[PDB]
Amino acid sequence: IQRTPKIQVYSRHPAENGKSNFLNCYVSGFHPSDIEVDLLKNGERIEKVEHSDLSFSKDWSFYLLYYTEFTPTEKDEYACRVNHVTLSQPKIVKWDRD
Amino acid sequence: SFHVIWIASFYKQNLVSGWLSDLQTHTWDSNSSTIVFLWPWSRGNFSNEEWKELETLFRIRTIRSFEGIRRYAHELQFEYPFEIQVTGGCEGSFLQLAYQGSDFVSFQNNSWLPYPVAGNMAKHFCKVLNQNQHENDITHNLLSDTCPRFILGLLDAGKAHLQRQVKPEAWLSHGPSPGPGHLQLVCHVSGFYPKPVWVMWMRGEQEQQGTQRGDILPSADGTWYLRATLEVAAGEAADLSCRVKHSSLEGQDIVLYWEGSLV
Ligand SMILES: CCCCCCCC/C=C\CCCCCCCCCCCCCC(=O)N[C@@H](COP(=O)(O)OCC[N+](C)(C)C)[C@@H](O)/C=C\CCCCCCCCCCCCC
């Protein structure tokens, strides 16, 4: 049985233009563990992204945290892009800020 | 509770790590085949020389277990690609194994038992797993003797880190998908530890029961994050506030008010 990833995107601190921050993409509830996760800046892949060691929950579904340090400007859009066997096409979830 | 998890993926990738619940405390380095300590106190009160003992059975059993799974895959009817997951530890002790993300077999007292629903495949697996009783007795003692002693030393050694209090910060934003004529108010709470937290949209002292709390999500620095949202009619968004309560604030709630440029 395959399980599709839940994808949640958030910043460590309130967004303030010109101030250093951390962008997070938490991917969870998926199976099998093979997965591809990119953080995007203006549709372009962000080069140095870190992730937690792969782990799983009680129901055996996997979860990973992806993150990077970043400084937002008013012109920049960020998102998390996920590909997994359960997905027809990569799924993109934007960082929502005001 | 302390537990070790094993993730093995076959198409031959292998991951072993140790956990205090959500908190990772140990990792296994394949290249060095060593036990990596993620915190100073991850050693617990286990002497430096006793730690190389533990590494030994971890040495031999991790790659004997990985190797063992692929020769038998034929008779066990494991078909590529597939994944095996194991979790074992103590709180009471446990050791459970899944095949393709479903309960498959578990270790109970002195032997491996198949989950009934897992069928004859799990039964044939247990036969293999139980073919040497001594190796099962070692598994028993690791769980009922070694694991309980370890977790005591671990908790004591880490007490400082584990009972620390880190204050949350919070902020408000507009949510993305309100229905027509309505707004979505979002209250973000971040940087708190430990995990339990209280957050509600309020009108004065009246809790707004429309408040929808999301999952509590991790940050890389080991603190936690939560979003709480409220859907309201645009006419009725006056006098709303977000109130955060947390052990670390000692009664001084964080309170933020919907207004300024938010309106
Ligand atoms: C990052 C590490 C942190 C460590 C911190 C430690 C502190 C706390 C310590 C302990 C807490 C509890 C941990 C629980 C560990 C439980 C160990 C599991 C026992 C494994 C059974 C080995 C059987 C074997 O090793 N099985 C070998 C048998 O080889 P053999 O030729 O010995 O068999 C011949 C026996 N006769 C002498 C009678 C002929 C294999 O061919 C069979 C079956 C393969 C299936 C095994 C895979 C499933 C094992 C599940 C566990 C795998 C990884 C566990 C470690 C993560």
Image (tube, coloured by chain):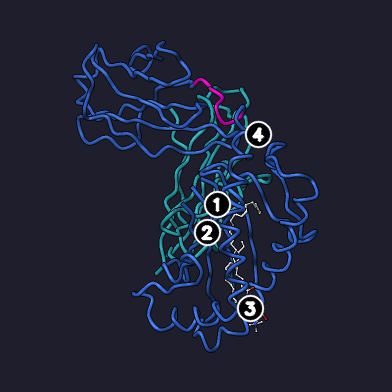
Chain colours: A cyan, B blue
Whether A62 is among the magenta residues is: no
Which residue type does callout 2 highlight?
Answer: Thr
Same chain, labels 3 and 4: yes
- Find disc 3 in the rendering and name its residue: B68
Which of the marked residues, 1 or 4, is nearer the chain's N terminus?
A: 1
Same chain, labels 2 and 3: yes
Query: What residue is drawn where x is 53% and y is 69%?
Result: B84
Badge 4 density bin: few <14, some 14–19, many ≥20, Cα 10 Å = some
What separation in Å lies between label 2 and label 4 (alpha carbons)?
23 Å
- Find disc 1 in the rendering and name its residue: B3
Same chain, labels 1 and 4: yes
- Find disc 2 in the rendering and name its residue: B87
In this rendering, which labeled residue sits more in front, label 2 or label 4? Answer: 4
The reply to whether discs 3 and 4 touch (Cβ–Cβ < 8 Å) is no
Badge 1 density bin: few <14, some 14–19, many ≥20, Cα 10 Å = many
Q: Main secondary structure of the magenta part?
A: loop
- Find disc 4 in the rendering and name its residue: B157
Same chain, labels 3 and 1: yes
Percent x, y of residue B142? 60, 58
The reply to whether discs 2 and 1 touch (Cβ–Cβ < 8 Å) is yes
Which of the marked residues, 2 or 4, is nearer the chain's N terminus?
A: 2
Question: What span is colored magenta in the figure?
Answer: B161-167
Task: Tell which of B141 and B48 is nearer to you.
Answer: B141
Secondary structure, mark 2, is strand
Which of the marked residues, 2 or 3, is nearer the chain's N terminus?
A: 3
Q: Is residue B29 left or right of residue A78?
A: right
Percent x, y of residue B136? 58, 70
In this rendering, which labeled residue sits more in front, label 3 or label 4? Answer: 4
The reply to whether discs 3 and 1 touch (Cβ–Cβ < 8 Å) is no
Same chain, labels 2 and 1: yes
Q: Chain of mark 3?
A: B
Query: What residue is drawn where x is 44% and y is 78%?
Result: B122
